[PDB]
């Protein structure tokens, strides 16, 4: 009976798109509770995590009389088809693979709704609650305890077949499902991702300092610390370095979902046109990816940084214009710093005037940096 519903569940989920499905109890995550406290004690959290730890570790708190959690995983493409090249005159920024195509929040929400629609169709007083959307449980912890994948040294849930290139979601039920078994850790003594990390955010195997992680830094709205401005590179959103360097991700590129296929002109877009994009055009071009949930402001800021990284002298006029005209202190200051970083002394005069007019001390401080660089 219960076993039968489980088999019909697995069978149906694979037919609608789910690449891997797992089962676990609705018991509390004791090891997670301690880790969250420990990570915060060191200040290693990102601030994007859910504040209340109690809700994060107690499945029975979110859903009364719950006895199981069903975890799913969807593999996403790692290689882009017909990707344009970042030429000298036309530099391009890059979005992380976890932001290629349609937002995985919407895709995974659609799959769980069907899975809930499936359980309700049986009409057996079944109660569920999708833990996607927002956002309390630890998707990684649930996945590991449901045999979806093992927690690798780069904090990534790594599947044997699809590697780490998978989106995770789960659904709490009141069904006495029989749990699966956590798979063996296949990292061994390898430490490639730890050394390959540009900022050394992976201070320890399976331990991340999110404050140093580029993936988090690209999503911040304030000024980026100078120690990271030269290490962000051309990344507009997210960072795939500790995944691409991984041997378990070698030869892993699944195109099993058409809506996940990246649009190469927005996945790897030209840097300069992003400097002059409206709110309307941004929501139209990028509003359907995951990397737009903070707005255009952090992305535009990273475009300026990426241009200063490339020293695109042809961007100097537009950078100059943003320094004087843009209503955002973060943009004005970043542009000014970029102008100095590019190293064209002809624009030194225009930095001077802005320094007089600027009232925001942080932006005023950034202008003084660009002046120094010349
Ligand atoms: C906050 C957040 C971030 C933060 C920090 C993530 C982090 N590493 O802690 C930032 C903004 C940096 C980030 C980055 C990324 N993230 Co993110 N992020 C989240 C979010 C909202 C919560 C994660 C969290 O609470 N982390 C806190 C840590 C402490 O716990 P945890 O990693 O979730 O759980 C593990 C640890 O606690 C560990 N742990 C427990 N006990 C112990 C004991 C020891 C000794 C050790 C060493 C570890 C350990 O085991 C748990 C299971 O693996 C989740 C969604 C969700 N609701 O879970 C997505 C999520 C984790 N992120 C995801 C993605 C895709 C990414 C990026 C790859 C995006 C990108 N391309 O840049 C990077 C990866 C960076 C990296 N190397 O880890 C996916 C992961 C998919 C997968 N297959 O695993 C998730 C699950 C979103 C989703 N729904 O699919 N993200
Ligand atoms: S996503 Fe990039 S910055 Fe963050 S831990 Fe991985 S390699 Fe380091
Ligand atoms: S690079 Fe090595 S240590 Fe890092 S996740 Fe891959 S196998 Fe594990």
Image (cartoon, rainbow, N blue to C red):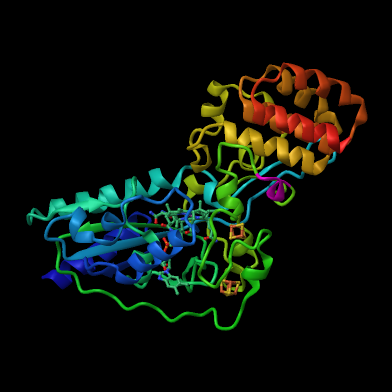
The residue depicted at 59 percent of the width and 21 percent of the height is: 278
The residue depicted at 52 percent of the width and 44 percent of the height is: 101
Q: Is residue 269 depicted above or below 284 in this figure?
A: below
Q: Is residue 374 depicted above or below 97 in this figure?
A: above
The residue depicted at 53 percent of the width and 46 percent of the height is: 99
**Residue 324: quadrant of the picture:** top right
**Residue 154: quadrant of the picture:** bottom right
Q: Is residue 361 visible?
A: yes
Image location (x, y in percent) of residue 204: 56, 71
Q: Is residue 322 depicted above or below 141 in this figure?
A: above
Image location (x, y in percent) of residue 48: 44, 48
What is the magenta range? 225-229
Q: Is residue 48 left or right of residue 195?
A: left
Quadrant showing the C terminus: top right
The residue depicted at 73 percent of the width and 16 percent of the height is: 357
Camera-nearest residue between 292 and 153: 153
Image location (x, y in percent) of residue 186: 51, 80
Camera-nearest residue between 254 and 91: 91
């Amino acid at each position: 009976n219960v076993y039968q519903l489980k088999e019909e569940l697995i069978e149906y989920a694979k037919s609608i798109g789910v690449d891997k499905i797992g089962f676990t109890t609705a018991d509390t995550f004791d090891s997670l509770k301690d880790r969250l406290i420990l990570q915060e004690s060191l200040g290693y959290l990102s601030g994007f995590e859910e504040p209340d730890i109690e809700k994060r570790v107690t499945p029975k708190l979110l859903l009364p009389k719950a006895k199981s959690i069903v975890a799913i995983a969807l593999a996403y493409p790692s290689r882009m088809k017909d990707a344009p090249r970042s030429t000298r005159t036309e530099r391009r920024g890059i979005f992380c693979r976890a932001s290629w195509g349609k937002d995985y929040h919407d895709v995974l929400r659609e799959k769980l709704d069907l899975l809930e629609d499936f359980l309700k169709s049986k009409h057996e007083d079944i109660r569920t609650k999708s833990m996607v959307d927002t956002g309390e449980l630890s998707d990684r912890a649930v996945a590991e305890r449901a045999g979806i994948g093992f927690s690798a040294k780069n904090c990534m849930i790594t599947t044997p077949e699809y590697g780490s290139y998978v989106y995770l979601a789960e659904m709490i039920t009141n069904i006495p499902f029989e749990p699966d078994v956590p798979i063996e850790d296949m990292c061994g003594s390898c430490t490639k991702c730890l050394d390959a990390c540009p900022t050394g955010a992976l201070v320890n195997p399976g331990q991340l300092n999110a404050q140093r992680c580029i993936s988090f830094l690209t999503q911040t709205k304030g000024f980026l610390p100078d120690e990271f401005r030269t290490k962000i590179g051309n990344r507009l959103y997210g960072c795939d370095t500790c995944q691409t360097v991984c041997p378990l991700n070698k030869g892993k590129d699944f195109h099993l979902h058409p809506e996940m296929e990246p649009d190469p002109e927005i996945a790897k877009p030209l840097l300069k046109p992003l400097l002059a994009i409206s709110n309307r055009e941004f929501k139209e071009k990028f509003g359907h990816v995951s990397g737009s949930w903070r707005g255009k402001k952090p992305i535009q800021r990273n475009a300026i940084l990426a241009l200063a990284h490339f020293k695109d002298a042809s961007a100097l006029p537009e950078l100059t214009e943003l320094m004087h005209k843009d209503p955002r202190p973060v943009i004005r200051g970043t542009a000014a710093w970029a102008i100095g970083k590019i190293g064209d002394p002809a624009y030194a005069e225009e930095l001077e005037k802005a320094l007089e007019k600027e009232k925001d001390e942080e932006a005023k401080l950034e202008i003084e940096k660009g002046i120094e660089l010349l």
